[PDB]
Image 1 (cartoon, rainbow over the protein chains, first blue to last red):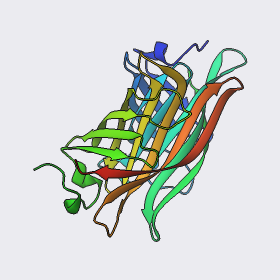
Image 2 (cartoon, rainbow over the protein chains, first blue to last red):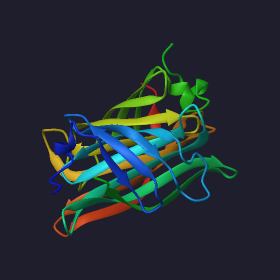
Image 3 (cartoon, chains in turn brown, green):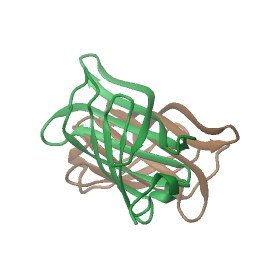
Image 4 (cartoon, rainbow over the protein chains, first blue to last red):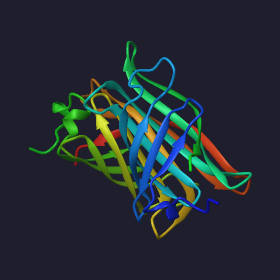
Length: 122
Length: 129
């Protein structure tokens, strides 16, 4: 099963959260993370198309972010996550995350927060 | 020429710039923002009673319009705090003429009780130099 994020370097992995948002991450030899994220969140803009992701990972923790602009649809917002690996009965793994969404609405800058759990899709 | 705070409209004003920002506990982020909004640089934790202080950690993210987001893992081959942090935030101009980033951070760490996640606020102030 899963040991650490570092050993993912060289193999693309795909991960899905409870909203059906999917991301595919590529890990460089220093734990730099790049990839793409496809939002499926209900009632949100920028659904179904790929957005660039970047971050960092090591051992059992990871942090990454997505700015919701890809030159096709611009949702004027950014989300960032931090999470830890959790191994599942029968050799799967999840990333248990906390996230923030920054956007500039009516009453100026606002931040909203919540949780996401990503499951590795072999 | 180089970044000037008076000429800041939003994060698009950081494209092709090199800037230093300090939060309320004197932790420091030094960021190079490329012509496309790509954020690279270094974060130095100075927060008392935390691990991994006074060493640069790699930081990466992206800046576009009014919002910014960036990530650090607290492992650099020198000191590993078994933790990761991400920030999302927005640009705020003061009538001072100063520039701030209001962020919320997400923290994940493995401690004696296993995996934990936390959230909080940081305000970063642009340093002239």
